Length: 257
Ligand SMILES: NS(=O)(=O)c1cc(C(=O)Cn2cnc3ccccc32)ccc1Cl
Ligand SMILES: [Zn+2]
Image 1 (cartoon, rainbow, N blue to C red):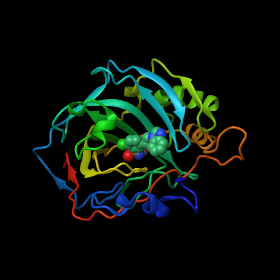
Image 2 (cartoon, rainbow, N blue to C red; image 1 turned 120 degrees about the horizontal axis):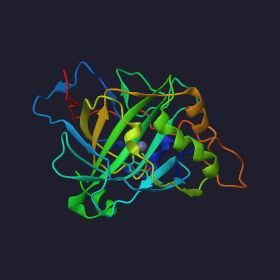
Image 3 (cartoon, rainbow, N blue to C red; image 1 turned 60 degrees about the vertical axis):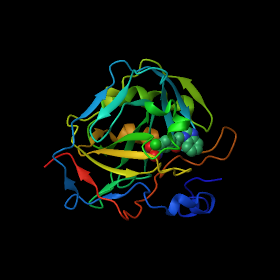
Image 4 (cartoon, helix red, strand yellow; image 1 turned 120 degrees about the vertical axis):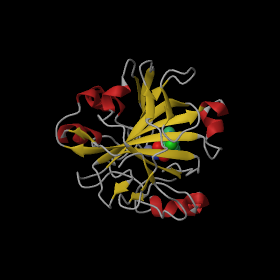
């Protein structure tokens, strides 16, 4: 039922998923002046050398690039985290226009898109069990601005036409997610939730300060995807972002400055 339209978009989600009005929902606006520098935060450890991508899927809300997470091959740890989190998938949120599309905002600035690298805590054995825990997931969020192309994104853009509609998938091996990271790993961090239903409050968010650049042609190709299935009327997959939610009783911490 849920999606991103007038009739089933974010302002409606709370009727099926009441935690939508919960105490630690995401995304949020990152007020850079009020984020607290925490000199005890560690450098983030991103260990993606052995990543095994498997498949790319149009799930009707975004596209997911999925990884083999049955061994410690692409892991996140350090930063604010206590254990080891395994990469399971990444996906993006983007706009119908370059001036919107990100979920998190920075001093109310919206980026053109936002990449989410989703990882689950190995102490819970699998993703489905991890999402039921308050420290189950760690999502590395990276902003995209439009400018020069991101060469490491082009393999993803080029397969999109093979997964245009809801439920399509394609083999997607040997994709290296290191090609999507900016130079700096400086970040903000706070406790939050999935940004899509079921909106579970299981995520440590780690949002990088430095955006990556992608070209206008690369983001245009995202906008040609479809939320509908094949043989259904065409609804362009655009504006699949949830707006900023109340910060409530939380403090955003900065690893820098
Ligand atoms: N947007 S996000 O908070 O990074 C996040 C998003 C998701 C998904 O959207 C995964 N996902 C894959 N098929 C789906 C069908 C309905 C809802 C979610 C679905 C799963 C985990 C995380 Cl952490
Ligand atoms: Zn997401």
